[PDB]
Amino acid sequence: MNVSIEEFTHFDFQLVPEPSPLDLVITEPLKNHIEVNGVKSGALLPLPFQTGIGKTYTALNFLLQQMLEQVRSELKEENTGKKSKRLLYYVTDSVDNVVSAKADLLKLIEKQTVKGEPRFTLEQQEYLKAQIVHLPNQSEQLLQCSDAVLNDVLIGFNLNAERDVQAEWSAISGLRRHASNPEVKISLNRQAGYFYRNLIDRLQKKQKGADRVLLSGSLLASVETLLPGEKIRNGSAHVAFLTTSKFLKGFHNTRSRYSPLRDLSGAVLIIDEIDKQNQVILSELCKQQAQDLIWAIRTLRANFRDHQLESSPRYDKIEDLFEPLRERLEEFGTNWNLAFAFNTEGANLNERPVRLFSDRSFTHVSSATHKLSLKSDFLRRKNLIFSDEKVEGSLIEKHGLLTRFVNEADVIYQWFLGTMRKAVFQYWENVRGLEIEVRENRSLEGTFQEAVQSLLTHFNLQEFESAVYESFDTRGLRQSAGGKANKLSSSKSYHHTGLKLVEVAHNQGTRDTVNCKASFLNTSPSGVLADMVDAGAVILGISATARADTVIHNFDFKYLNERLGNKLLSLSREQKQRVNNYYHSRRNYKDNGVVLTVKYLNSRDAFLDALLEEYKPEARSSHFILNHYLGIAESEQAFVRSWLSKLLASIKAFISSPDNRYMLSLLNRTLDTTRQNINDFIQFCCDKWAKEFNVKTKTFFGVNADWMRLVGYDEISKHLNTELGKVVVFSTYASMGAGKNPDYAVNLALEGESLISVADVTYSTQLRSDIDSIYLEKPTQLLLSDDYSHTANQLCQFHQILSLQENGELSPKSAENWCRQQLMGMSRERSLQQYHQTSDYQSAVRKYIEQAVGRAGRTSLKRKQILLFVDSGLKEILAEESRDPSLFSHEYVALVNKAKSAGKSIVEDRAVRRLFNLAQRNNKDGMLSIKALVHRLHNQPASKSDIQEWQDIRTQLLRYPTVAFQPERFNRLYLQSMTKGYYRYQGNLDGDPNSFEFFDRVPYGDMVSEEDCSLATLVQNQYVRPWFERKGFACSWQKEANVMTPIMFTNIYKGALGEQAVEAVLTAFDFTFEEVPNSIYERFDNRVIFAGIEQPIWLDSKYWKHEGNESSEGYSSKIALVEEEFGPSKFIYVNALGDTSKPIRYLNSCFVETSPQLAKVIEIPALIDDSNADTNRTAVQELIKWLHHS
DNA sequence: CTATTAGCCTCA
């Protein structure tokens, strides 16, 4: 063997095969994106290819070209530069597809001709083939080695000294030797897995430090054979084939486990059937474990209280990012007094658990009759959760709720889980360049497990290693993006926020205790894909329905377009036309006389009754016949009659047609031994109809994936090409997802003359035909379900409901009602009924029909006639398709055209409903967020972040009141309106948020526009306009379809618009303004100082003459607090745009006029006239005079 | 107080 890299010197890198029209479509947008964006950037190419035209071949050609380019590039640099190789992947969901793709790639490597001459020599082929690895699961991995290989590994490492390992190997080898029956293979697989778990563990244990066994010669080859992932690390190979489940786990090498998700720079991924990966990623997310919310609190509070005294090298600036966590923990623990245990006070009220659910933004649903509160009792020394007094009023509780405690515990846990990523990132930052203690090169992936293990070690929290690994990376990838906070100043969405679920059931072990379980979902598959693209990976997805219009059975492409932007590449019209021309050229139906017939059939009762009476003539009634001989009950009569009649009519219609040989009837249930009576009835009918004509028919029942893997699909192939007749196959929609390629060999002797080829050019390979008659039934339940545990199904259902609400297919009222009904127990029937009223159902049904139709037919030998039978319930759904028919299959368009001819149909646009629902949701979220922020601002001391948030919101609303383009950062402050610049609404901003009406539905409601806020009259002032120009505020409203929500037009805009006006007017007459000293924030406008006078004057401003229900003790409390904290002082109450003809009242602490000398509050009616835009010098003159000795 | 079920890969 002389396989070396240097061999490729004498080989021309200029001859290429003929570029197909399907090839430039992949290379051109990539080049455009490279020249527009940077060299190191991500992308996403949803390629809508079609079955039977070639999708795997093009991807394999692309992979081969990339490998050749890498090999070419590696030779040039040689010595002047050393780095790693590019990584390339091929990921799917099925093992058979993986092995078939690898075999096809290898075969393509062997055989390839340019101008009738082999492209590569034998040594070149060997070198290329020595670069691809395949990584199956561990248990199957152990069953491909040999005795000599594993013996060599054991002897080289000096492991043939313990009797246990050798005994286990001998037992496994013997059991493998004698293993033919199907009930011992499971034990063999389990034993192989458990042996592989310990072996690689020992190999890593020995060599992760001293006494490193050198690898060379044949021992290196043996270790590489046993560990395919070892070849990648050293640099031997840089191409991998694996499944999606393995991709999210990683593969082992001699040092540790390498996770592909954690190092994706300069990598290329190829995923086929990309739309189906949504459910796989959802299952992987939902398979997570739960966690009791009070055991970890105790462990974290007790084991982190005090530590030892040892800094040591390596560690540097790790404790600095942990002190705030302890500060928060102590503050949280010294409020509820969590040291005490938990109990409940109720008179036999623990039969059933109180579930608690939350969305973390604006949705909160509980299944308790009355709200529960938490209290601390100093008598019994225990914390209790109780409903307290049931009497009306009597000092109703307002301190807090259990939901608040749950949310606080959850946010504490999330913050703890999140700080470790930054700590480890800083640790690798100092290690890499700031330490250089050991010469190892490597990246974050190399020194990852050691750091987390050591830290779990330093603070000893080992029982948390599994909890922290799931959500560990360099930065994010599983939690939020951008601002990394759930605030109004950052982009908000469900796809990177998640949900929460908490249950309170009875606690066993100790009867006088309660438990609090929790399940989490930190992200959604769309967010995961977005993070993968952002990290710097080029993703290329191949599928035929990659851009479906559903969020249950597909990715949410509306969210990806608002986060990626220019990195989501799309094709133009010319490229689609070229693809369309290629597909017609390769499959031409407007020639050779190929025709399709489509027929919708209904249900009949005389037909079935006559057939039943002919079946058993000894009986008197059909009801007795069905109740006695068949297994159906009294309830199941109409449904069985309908579907059986439809199937029998379709079968009879097919049998009547002479020139046909194949039939596949897609159904929704499997026809097995459980339905033997119905099978016998169908067989009798088939025999009768075969006798009526002159044909021989053979029927196949119970065709499952198990039947495919036990008997095989080749039985039909032999039966079709040896004996003349007709074949009928019974199967299911889901069954034809694991068994592919339903073809068979042809025979010109047995077949007639109707085998016309459809391709316009000569066709290579063998001769094969496909199905020429199919029966389609209306699909049933399309709500995803999980059968792993009890919590996974509930998590899936809540995720589906939240996604449906977020997309815009559900109003907040309907979503809340559905969540409440599901939380407290629901049946599948009610869930399906609720789901049937949306617009996603029709899209899902249409996608299912298109996928089912497309998979039938992969050859060029089509019969003269093809018959299609469709259920009568699909007419309305298939009659409402209005996309463009450019990439449609030749049979789906026929269905649409036939269904559309049934009269004229009224179609209601989804847009109007989407805009209405989104406006409602935005208004509700704004209301709740503003209320929460205002409540937070009133708890002294006020945080710095809250003040920054408030100021940024006010400044953004002042500067830009109408944005032309869709905002990205300040997202949920605007709503899209049909009219530009103004809109109408109707609601009360004191009650139920989901009771608002918008736009055309109310023509006599309140108005939000520029003419209502009185902007022009204010702007005309000569003392205010220069201020507005200096600060850059808007002097007029632009005309675009993005306006602020009604909540922001009344409680935010008016106040600022008045405040700046009064400040600008008053600042000229020797007045200065300051900021509130953080103690009474939001209770007053500014602080006023002038001429160095005692008792500093506070200012309060309002925009217009607003009367509110504030005559209660709120004003007295405010004035008392100000007087206590600052002594005697003076206060100014100012309005704007009123009447400059009303005198000035002198007020005491209350609003009753008193003596001018003994006065503290000034009520100034107005300063700027609303008629000619004048001002009021007399008012300010009297103001200045009043500040004197009086 | 309505609709009407089959398939899957990985590891503690």
Image (tube, coloured by chain):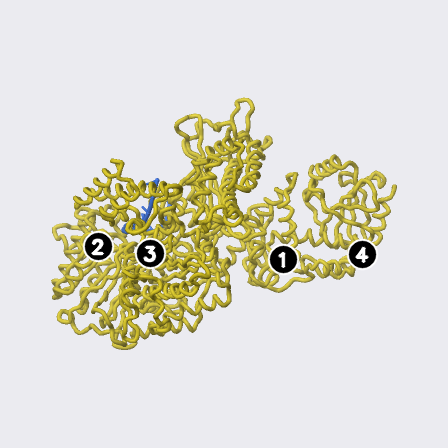
Chain colours: A yellow, B blue
Question: Which mark is in front, 1 or 3?
Answer: 3
Which corner quadrant holds the N terminus of chain A?
bottom left
Q: Chain of mark 1?
A: A
Q: Is any atom of residue A669 visible in this view?
A: yes
- Identify the amino acid type marked 4: Thr
Q: Nearer the viewer, mark 4 or mark 2?
A: 2
Give the number of the mark in front: 4 or 3. 3
Task: Identify the residue position indicated by label 4 in the image.
Answer: A1175
Which residue, given by chain and number where applicable, does mark 3 sit on? A241
- At numbered mark 3, what does the secondary structure look like: helix, strand or loop? strand
Residue extending farthest top: A379
Across and down, in percent, residue A288 comes to: 40, 43
In the rendered image, which residue does mark 1 sit on? A1008
Residue labelled with disc 2: A708
Q: Earlier in the sequence, mark 4 or mark 2?
A: 2
Q: Secondary structure at mark 2?
A: helix
What kind of residue is marked 2?
Met
SS category of the residue bearing label 1: strand
* Quadrant housing residue A582: bottom left
* Camera-side residue of A1109 and A826: A826
Q: CA distance from mark 1 to mark 4?
A: 27 Å
- In the rendered image, residue A635, in percent from the top left (x then y), is placed at 27, 46
* Amino acid carrying mark 3 in the image: Phe
Q: Nearer the viewer, residue A419 or A1128?
A: A419
- Left or right of A1092? Residue A258 is left
Distance Cα–Cα, label 4 vs label 3: 79 Å
